[PDB]
Length: 152
Ligand code: HEM
Image 1 (cartoon, helix red, strand yellow):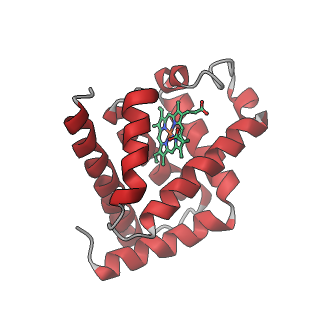
Image 2 (tube, rainbow, N blue to C red):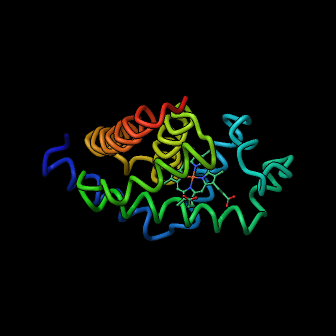
């Protein structure tokens, strides 16, 4: 449950991401994969990436980063009214990709890390609070769908 002012902060922060969705998406995934190498194993199409240099050079990783952040941005712009947008992602990530909710926590924190890394001094405490709450809401609603599906 975010207030109007918190959603305003989220969407203000998101404008930073939308200015360079592929660069943000790439760095989010690289942060996830390097911070939590087990997550790489969930991607048949990225498990060949042995080094961060290879990840950085991967155009397909940037492409997927764009897909991920485009989806997330579409969800965030719903300001919590995202049941229709979230449902297929929860279902695909539970049933097809088999992504534990822990990895969604990892990527949530990776987003925060990337925002500070790319916008040092420009991702204020209020913005971090609001973005964190929005990612928690996202993760929590996914978690509810995971529970429905019995997925761990
Ligand atoms: C912000 C969180 C995330 C969003 C918005 C997101 C979004 C997406 C989207 C839109 C797709 C393609 C459509 C689909 O299959 O449903 C996708 C595919 C996938 N996602 Fe995610 N995802 C997220 C987090 C994760 C995490 C944390 C993992 C694994 C650690 C993961 C693993 C995958 C895999 C394995 C695929 C299929 C990739 C392929 O083979 O093309 N996702 N994701």
